[PDB]
Length: 60
Image 1 (cartoon, rainbow, N blue to C red):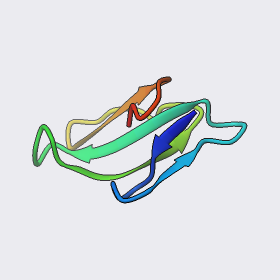
Image 2: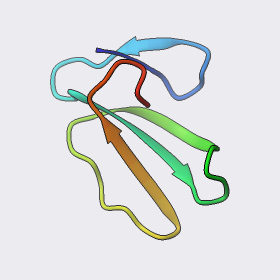
Image 3: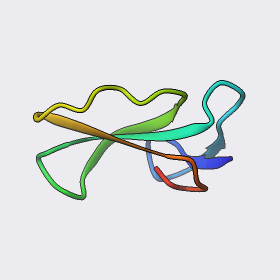
Image 4: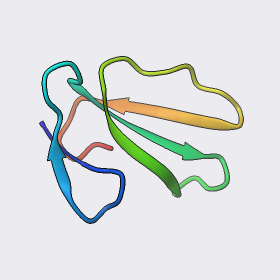
């Protein structure tokens, strides 16, 4: 799987372990991420910040 890295400047492939791309963004905006990467399990979603997971190309 080839997802995007933290900054939308380059892309990287999630190696074994992280078969799901994650994206961490603040409620500050509905479309304003702070940082992203690759992970295996999705963390708990809070009111302050929320996280989304997806097993697709350039999902995060």
